[PDB]
Image (tube, coloured by chain):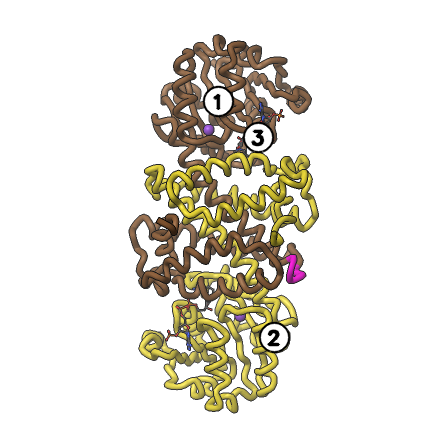
Chain colours: A brown, B yellow
Amino acid sequence: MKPSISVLGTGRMGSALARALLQAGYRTVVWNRTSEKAEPLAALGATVAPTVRQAIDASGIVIVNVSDYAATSTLLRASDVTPGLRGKLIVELTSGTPEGARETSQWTAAHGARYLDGAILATPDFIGTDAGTILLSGALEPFAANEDVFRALGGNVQHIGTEPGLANALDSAVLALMWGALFGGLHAIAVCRAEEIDLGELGRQWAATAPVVEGLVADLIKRTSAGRFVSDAETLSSISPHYGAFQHLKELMEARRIDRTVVDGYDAIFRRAIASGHLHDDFAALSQFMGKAEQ
Amino acid sequence: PSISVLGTGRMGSALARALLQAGYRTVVWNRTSEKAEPLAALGATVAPTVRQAIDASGIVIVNVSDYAATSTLLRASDVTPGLRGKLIVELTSGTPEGARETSQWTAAHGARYLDGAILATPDFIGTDAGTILLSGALEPFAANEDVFRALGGNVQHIGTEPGLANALDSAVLALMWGALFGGLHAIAVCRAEEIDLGELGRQWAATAPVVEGLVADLIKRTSAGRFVSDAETLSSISPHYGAFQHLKELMEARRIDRTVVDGYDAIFRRAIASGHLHDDFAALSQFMGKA
Ligand SMILES: NC(=O)c1ccc[n+]([C@@H]2O[C@H](COP(=O)([O-])OP(=O)(O)OC[C@H]3O[C@@H](n4cnc5c(N)ncnc54)[C@H](OP(=O)(O)O)[C@@H]3O)[C@@H](O)[C@H]2O)c1
Ligand SMILES: NC(=O)c1ccc[n+]([C@@H]2O[C@H](COP(=O)([O-])OP(=O)(O)OC[C@H]3O[C@@H](n4cnc5c(N)ncnc54)[C@H](OP(=O)(O)O)[C@@H]3O)[C@@H](O)[C@H]2O)c1
Ligand SMILES: [K+]
Ligand SMILES: [K+]
């Protein structure tokens, strides 16, 4: 076939989604409240639909990419547009909860629309590339039928199961890692700022040292999955040296008036693990001490 | 040159093996001497005391719990007289003031000093990727570049000022712990949403380069003062905060300790309270100071 495809939301992402569809030779129609933010996509060859309704019935698949499900829900569940959803495919690529996916599934189905709920595990620069990862959950047929449309967004766009909440559950897990790393960087930058270290140096040192962290994270997951909490020949780090080295960071942050709210959080997990006889056990032991302290 | 390693831990053992593999006469000491016996068979000499170890070799690499422990091994009246003409390489984790103090005391006993941060797990010592940052005097590094190359292909001298290594160590380890506590969270979520950790594993493999781009971008942008949104930003604060809500709610609901994420929240809210809701993620770097 080669359908017409609509994108609702011309944000930073969404704009990317749209450009990636234009670059693969799909007729792409775009709507955005604050329509001036959608003008750039006109020049790249998209048609700028004046309203949601015009957009959702100008195309046979509709990709949504706005703030949250609350905003999706006010665009698509309006009496204005709900009648037009018949036979269309809604692909909800906005960040949401698994209950949010299950609700949006049920109301789209109730208006004669097919539903795919998706988590974009990728920044704008990755949409269009063979590396671009988007996880989609929902019915299989509407995915299988349009594999060509999904390939235009990324080479690593995958269908992961029937149950439509699955994509967002996974999204929340992966985003937990992403924020850990990023708030790690925010700390790293605050330390460098305090000890008058050029961030260029931090940059070129992270380039070199990132693979070590990747090994460490991968190890955490492998070991936790296997219940290998006790120290053994294969562990690369025990809690003792982590906690020992960590002290030096706390003291530095205390001295330099850097917010400790986050690291005091780490401390509490360490101390919980050490309170059980885990001082000299693999870093993965910490995974058993993730629940709330008070009971 | 004969080379001594004090501390045959998990690391240190690695340091020792890497020296033996490059054909250095390596002597090793460890309290609880049975933990150093394995290195005998790979060709190390297990010195019964610290003193015998530090005057059996001309460079001494230290790798124990903390500077307090280094200081009780080397500043004992037993051994301090033997430190003359030696090079102490302190590769144990410590503070920058700790480096500056250990510099001054070693110099006062006629010893040369390099303070080092090992930015690598044991498996990376011996490999071209192995990264160790050394600060201290240049000559004692330059003179022994071959000894450092045996520990890693990415072993660097970064400045005269001897605290520099540990300052940088604390910054880099902040990133490392961010990621790892990120994983611990990611695992708690997976456990709650009945996701097999294998799935998390193979999804992080795929998705890690995205995070690497994001972290590298943070640093490049912060260094350049590019806090305001522009054509080149891949993420603004708004969508981060929006998606973050879904994580907080999940952890609240599943009785997962929120001490950490409430910490993130506070930084977001501080950035948003200034007109930075739709600015690059890097803007958050300006809201890292206390209350
Ligand atoms: N940025 C990334 O790298 C990335 C990656 C993965 C996931 N995501 C997800 O992708 C989505 C898009 O993020 P983004 O970076 O594109 O954000 P953004 O540039 O800040 O734009 C948000 C978009 O949502 C629209 N919107 C917001 N509130 C709305 C409302 N109440 N009613 C209608 N439309 C509304 C905006 O229209 P207006 O112009 O009128 O505000 C705009 O099109 C988010 O759900 C985010 O969680 C983003
Ligand atoms: N593991 C890593 O990947 C890694 C990363 C970078 C740097 N480091 C740093 O390297 C150092 C060692 O780490 P590790 O993994 O080897 O820790 P570890 O396996 O627990 O070993 C600690 C070593 O320090 C010795 N030690 C501790 N307190 C001592 C004292 N009071 N007197 C004498 N020796 C003492 C221990 O002696 P005993 O064995 O008899 O107890 C042992 O040899 C730490 O500063 C750590 O922060 C480690
Ligand atoms: K979604
Ligand atoms: K050190």
**Which chain is mark 3 on?**
A
Instruction: Single out the mark in the foreground, 3 or 1.
Output: 3
Residue type at numbered disc 2: Arg
Residue type at numbered disc 3: Met
Instruction: Single out the mark in the foreground, 2 or 1.
Output: 2
Q: CA distance from mark 2 to mark 3?
A: 49 Å
State the image coordinates of residue B171 (x, y, percent, origin top left).
57, 58
Q: Main secondary structure of the magenta part?
A: loop
State the image coordinates of residue A92 (x, y, percent, origin top left).
47, 24
Q: What secondary structure is marked by label 3?
A: loop
In the rendered structure, find residue A13 and report the number of the disc placed on it. Answer: 3
Q: Residue at x 49, y 11 (%)?
A: A82
Q: Is residue B183 visible?
A: yes
Q: What secondary structure is marked by label 2?
A: helix
Q: Are both tags, 2 and 1, on one chain?
A: no
Extent of the magenta region? A193-197
Q: In terms of depth relative to the viewer, which is nearer, A227 or A41?
A: A227
Q: Are marks 2 and 3 in contact (CB under 8 Å)?
A: no
In the rendered structure, find residue B85 and report the number of the disc placed on it. Answer: none
Q: In terms of depth relative to the viewer, which is nearer, B261 or B179?
A: B261
| Drawn side of residue A144 relative to residue A183, left or right | left
Q: Residue at x 61, y 75 (%)?
A: B100
Q: Is residue A292 magenta?
A: no
Q: Earlier in the sequence, mark 3 or mark 1?
A: 3
> On the image, numbered disc 2 is attached to which residue?
B100
Residue type at numbered disc 1: Val
